[PDB]
Amino acid sequence: SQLADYQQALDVQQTRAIQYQQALQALERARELCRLPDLSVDNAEEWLETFQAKEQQATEALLALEQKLSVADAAHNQFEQAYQLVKNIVGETSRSEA
Amino acid sequence: QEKIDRYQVDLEELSYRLEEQTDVVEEAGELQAEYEARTEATEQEVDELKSQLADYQQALDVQQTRAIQYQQALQALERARELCRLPDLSVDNAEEWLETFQAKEQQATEALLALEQKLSVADAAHNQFEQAYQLVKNIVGETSRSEA
Amino acid sequence: QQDYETAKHSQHQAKQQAFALVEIVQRRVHFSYSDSAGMLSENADLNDKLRQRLEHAESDRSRAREQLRQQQAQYSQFNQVLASLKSSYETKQDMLKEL
Amino acid sequence: QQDYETAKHSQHQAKQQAFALVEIVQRRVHFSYSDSAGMLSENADLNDKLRQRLEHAESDRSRAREQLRQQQAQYSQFNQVLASLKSSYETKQDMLKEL
């Protein structure tokens, strides 16, 4: 279309050049946030999938942490009653092993 | 003896069904190949028209003289006047508007990430809820989530 | 998910708006010589008629592609039911000879 | 609670870093515009550079079309053999039920 419509007068070329500067600016911002001075458009997918796995581990972990904090609302009496019930059945056991 | 006869009749019926589907597949294959040649011919026609248009304009658009170049700045400014709710937008005050809209863009990314953290834990929690529900359905069959 | 989708649309519009403002800043130098002028529309008639024939060809190419994709789809389902029939016939034949 | 607030802060670090890298993945096509930026710096007749960039793109597109055609044929063949196995399982299952 640029070759057929040369009356376009480099407007798309200016847009593509400004987009190239925007791509370079974004890459520099990512090298700073990720602290990776050694980076390229061709190998950035390797660090992205690595950090996606890191984010998946953080979200999957934090999900289990959210369920644990949600059940932690139970008062002191339920823990004591359950712990003493186990101790009366099996004998002395640690609270962690109960 | 009757079972062998029934299987022979089933093979005759399957042969009739095969003949009908082979005829349908052959007609569909001819239409597919004809539409392929026609579609490739439409891209070839589009490329021929684009190339002939390029060849025809060669002497017209080469002598641009850097005079028809500023209208692009005017069109960019006008495009921004519709896209950005700023009827008074001028190339002079566009720097204050640029930093003001960049502030809105970073605020939008921060709000997007803030929503994304809760969204990720919620989507995964629903995936485990669905897994528990599928496991219950595989073991007993249909039942409500309240009964799960 | 609806709120995050709305936030993603809002972010896309904000990014597009910020980019339109960056283009104005880059084009301030081009606006400086806005007093200049030159020749235009000498051979515009044939160029516009040829552009219209090209739009007809691109729209017809779009129709041609749509008819091509839907035909590939029905042909694939026809080939799939035919392959299902072939295997059913072959296995029923193998079972008749086994019987 | 101390370990959990630390996990929440760690999740924010991962989200901002991944978001930045994801933006560069969207900008993948924009890095190819380095030729367009060099072309823009010509400031004179450049139709030869435009045609050279296009011929390279035509060569890449033709190789991609051939690659797509042979993969589509291979995928269709794999789809017909899969359907042949499905139909063979159905006839073997019906024969088991009949027996």
Image: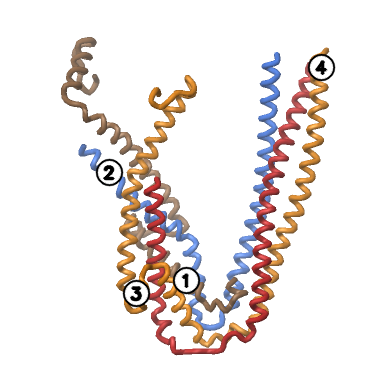
Chain colours: A brown, B orange, C red, D blue
The C terminus of chain C is located in which quarter?
top right
Local secondary structure at mark 4 = helix
Amino acid type assigned to the residue bearing label 2 in the image: Lys
Spatial distance from mark 4 to mark 2, Cα to Cα? 70 Å
Task: Chain letter for mark 1, please.
Answer: A
Front in this rendered view, residue B126 or A61: B126
Residue C47, relative to residue A97: is it above or below?
Answer: below
Tell me whether the residue at label 1 lies in contact with that at label 4, contact meaning CB atoms closer than 8 angstroms.
no
The residue that mark 1 highlights is A15
The residue that mark 4 highlights is B4
Front in this rendered view, residue C48 or A64: C48
Question: Residue at 40% across / 75% down in the picture?
Answer: C24
The residue that mark 2 highlights is D8
Amino acid type assigned to the residue bearing label 1 in the image: Thr
Any mark on residue B94, and which? 3
Local secondary structure at mark 3 = helix
- Pair 3/1: label in front: 3
Q: Residues within 10 Å of mark 2 (few under 14, many from 20)?
A: some
Amino acid type assigned to the residue bearing label 3 in the image: Ala
Residue B71, relative to residue B100: is it above or below?
Answer: below
Spatial distance from mark 1 to mark 4, Cα to Cα? 75 Å
In-image side of A41 versus C73 (left or right): left
